[PDB]
Length: 207
Length: 210
Image 1 (cartoon, rainbow over the protein chains, first blue to last red):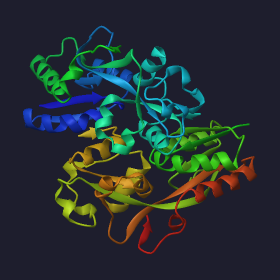
Image 2 (image 1 turned 90 degrees about the vertical axis):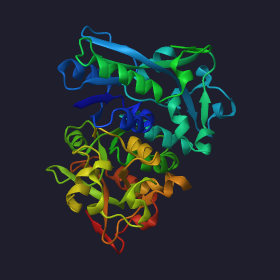
Image 3 (image 1 turned 180 degrees about the vertical axis):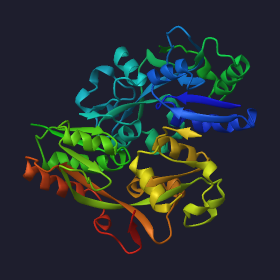
């Protein structure tokens, strides 16, 4: 059997290094092909039958499509040494200068969700991060990247103040996805690839 | 009015941080808008007036455009501590295990040029994801030379160069031939050139243009 799984561009770099070795082991001999695509293409590709499963960061909200919770993940500030905020320890929404702020394009759920809760187009998170580490402005990253960060990269992280926003990362498939056993096991491996505390919302956190 | 400039995604994260503050000091009061795009799109955007300049990794070679050299840039290997090839000090493309190799999709000139010149699971992947995977001990990927000055000491341990001849690409600034602000254009060329080590300005012994 072959398995076609899409993943968001803002999830893949941080989740995939973790799940690859688990897949390798618990799903031995299953040939899996991974594809990065934004959310709407994911929904569209599930429906068309191009992909089997989708790791996205919201509820599908469309007939034919069902999604299960996998884990919650916070939004974290990434602040350059020459910003006034650098000297504070948590991000203050109100003090953030929007002319010095790197945001992804509309259509990335990561950006859509952050703008609700609270110069350079087409940007990647890689680009924004490199800019901040060299003194240029502020961007936002997902919690799961800090574990990949060097100790001096870690010095630039600033969490939000309570209430701290989280996005929910979910697995999506077609309602009548024929392979109900595979789908459940996966929900099992993916949830297993991240810390257990993330499996549950927490006081101070709110979607 | 303002400058609309496009930039390859295989260039922006490594070059934009160097040039940004030099653009501020020297071109004060000039409002710049940067957009990340792949090569074909840069070209069609110049022709159609959507952007004014594009920083690409080849000669435009299209009716109506022209371009100037900015610098040369090696392709580099990025090898995880678990791969067989990690023991070697130079990488050979012909020995790379294809099942443990991450590559950008066709249409990304960084992959298209490498594959052609060197005559050599995961689609739609980003350079960031490929590097994260390699750091975690999984596979091999290729990186542009200018990214090394952003790498920690531990990350640098994974870099492996090619053996002679080493392949480089040329980074160039393309515009419309009828382009208006011809002064702003030579200023920029200077600023961009000054944003990279002087060794990259000319083709060095042992480098061949891919």
